[PDB]
Every structure is written in C-alpha cells, then in structure tokens.
Image 1: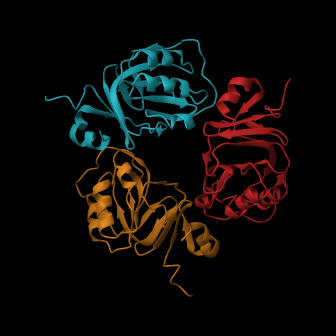
Image 2: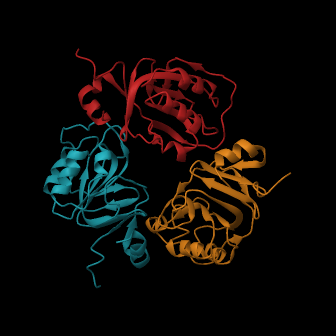
Image 3: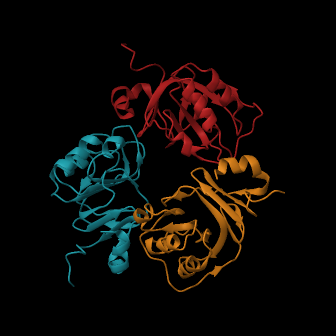
Length: 161
Length: 161
Length: 161
C-alpha cells in the first residue's frame, strides 16, 4: 500500500504524479479503482459521481487547479463515507477542511477555499483527465499516501502476470 | 464562524483573501474587528498596537510579505493573550512558532524567520492595507479559519438589515 | 537551541538559510557539526556518510532540489538513529515520511517523492555546498528548529571569545 514500495516493484508500469497534494482526510493512505470527473469551478457532477460510483472507488477530479472555489465540502465528503468510497483526489480546492479531517476517508487537494462552486452541471464524467504530468483513465488504479500518488493501469496487487 | 458558511450567506458583502496563510496559533478559528498596521521589516508599531487595541481585536499587519525578518514572536503573542485579543494576521513572517502554537490565540502568517525585525518605529497604524487581493479597513470585521479568511465591512452576526 | 535566540545573540556570525524546509522527523529541533554530501538523484554517498560520520553529526545533503527521486528513506533514517546522528537536512526529497515521523531524529527536506534514487555512487562527500543562500562547510555547525535553520562556523555554545 506504500507508494514507495509500489514504485520499487512496479515503477515501469506506473505513472507518478508530479503535483504535490495536501492531505485533508482522516485517512492518509488510500487506493482503489479510478472514477473521473472533469470540471471547472462547478461541482454538480462531482456530487452525482459520489452518489453513484461503486464502493471502494477513488474519485479523481480535475478542477484545473482553480483556487477560486471549493469543489468538495463536508456534505459531499459525508456521502463518500456513507457509500464506502476510498477517497477523492482533487486538482483544485476543498472547504470544511476541519470537518473532513475527522472523517475516515482520503482527501487530497491543492488548497482550501471557502467559496462554494457553481452548480450548473457543466463538465463531464468518465473522461480521460490530464494533470500533474499524469493521464488519469477510468478503470485505472490509484495509490496514495504521505509520500505521493501513483497510478497503474490495473490492480497491481491482484495480478500474476 | 465558519468562513464557508459566511460565504454562502454573505458572499456579496465579503472580500475573500487570495493569499493562503499558514496557521500558527493554538486557535485555528478566530474573528473580530480589524485594527491595522503597515510596516516593512520593523515591528515597533506592531508591539504598540498589541499593547493598545481593544479586547477581541484582530490585528492585521501588512509586512509586504517580507521573509527576511519575523514581525511577531512569543513575547508579543503573549501580550495578545494577556490583553484578550482575538488574533493576528500577518502578511509576513513570525518566529517562536513552537511557543505560539501552544497559545490560545489565532496567528496566521506566510512563513517563519528566526531573524528579529528592525526596531525603528517606521510604518503606520490605522491606515488602509492592500494585500492578498483585499482592502483591509480599520473597523472592518475579519473571520478566519482552516478554510480561509474573509472580510466584511461590519459585524455580520449582529446585523438585521 | 532556538534559532530565534541564536540570531539575537550571534547574527553577525551566522548564515540564515533562505530555503524553507518541511520537517519530517520525530525531532523538530536539532543541531550539531556539519558533514556534507553533494549529489544529484543518487544516494549511495548519502548512505555511506550516514554509516560513517561521528555521533551527533547533522548530515547536510545538496540534492539540487530535485523532486524526481527521494534521497533518504526509512532504512537510512534508521541507520541515522542507530548511530546516534542528530539529523539530516536535504536540498531534495525523501520518502517513507510516515515512518520517519515516528523516529527520534531531525529530518528536513523540500518535499516527498516515492521514487527511489539512483545507486551509482556519483557525487562527492566533504565538499563545500551552496544552496538556500548559504555556504555549508564541513566542520561548521548547524542549528535547526520550527522557525528555520542557521549555520555558524563553530560551536556557538562552547565558545568564550
């Protein structure tokens, strides 16, 4: 589960995120199949994804790194906990960081912003994301911890060759 | 008291600081009427302000974001505690961060620096400050927490319209 | 031992590091005689240094600030603990930060990276390093804590004039 160990064993099959994230959730280490959301200062699709993706999923949200609004708050983090998701990785900001820090889920983002995001529904789910020098594909697997975030095109702990 | 809630209710009457601060005090959430100090690597006026502003005040210090010296240390933070101030927000650095982290007051700054600031008394108090994309006016109200810092031109929790 | 106090008393004999470090070890405050290592994404010499420098030493490693690989992990940090070193300061990244945070040693670096460094042995030990606006010389003394890092050309707490 350590990204350090995964790199030592499978570096050739891994993409290493170049963007350093701040860890906000109660869980510092988390991993699972990737579900994607591509938005810009709007989180309606982030919410719909959290309410529908399979348990154990790690939702990756490309918010273009905007710091003008938060894309996830305690209400949405709560949904993630209630539906048994592994965590959320956001190329953007979150809010209610105090409350999220007390939840048993992983949450990584580049910063905090108290302003709510737009609620128009613009953006798309299940598309290929591109940020942090990494190509995030639906169905791929992401592993995150205190040292970083790495992505594999399949479950590296269920393979045999 | 949450900046997230204040933005949802009063965004149109609020200024949202664009500069992310590091939180150093024992209190992560604090708010109150603003008192201003405008200086450059000198903290004599910061000290005089802390020794004279009314209880509950949040001292906002524009140190131009300099990282060459600290503008507040444990002695001054102690004064802030003894006189019942709400906290201090500094566009600059502080020192004695270890000691300040144990004090029941809010302290936000952009970094730490072990070097003491000049003691010449240059600068001015009670002037309008301009940094972080925000206009900080004396008498205005500031609310700070783990998600950010927002400024209103009056007490938003004592108003009725 | 506080960098703030050292600056107040000996600023004229001190070099103040301009590069802000993240603190990863169980010890937030540490100091001692400097041992140097100059490398670039390779840590064989970092390991050899940790296995040979005198107890109480603070190993300073100039990794050119690279964020592509880690230069120190839990194995090497463990060696530092077993041989009684004071700490390590790295102009580069580390990994196994979770594990290192539980160790009684000082560790400062600019970030984390899960990828292992090269093991070719390129680089040099006991040379003068130059980074963070500071000239790091073998035999010099370094003092580090929550506020910063300062370097003196001799033990400032064993001198008399």
